[PDB]
Image (cartoon, rainbow, N blue to C red):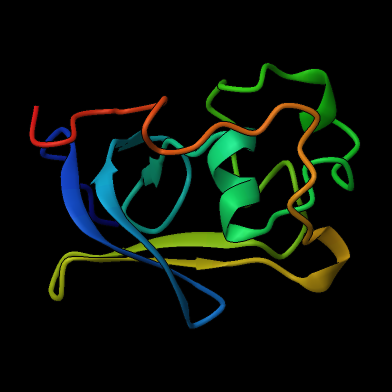
Length: 115
């Protein structure tokens, strides 16, 4: 048991040990080891390459709505390396694609980009 959301942080975002993006990230009490989960949406997840149309649920949410990762999808995960300032995400091939029935870049979701 741990918890420490300071209310947004800026990190290098990482998925399946590949790099993704370098943007601000909001993360808050939910359900993980630190309690805290990142806010990630069907837009943003599909930039990384999550098949929002595979998970029989996210395709019924909004284009930018907060969507879980360890929950919506099976065996995907999200962790904060607060030692190294890095967002560690995991997603199996069973739910990976870019096609989001929507999709929005990080310039149009802008959570607190040095703001």
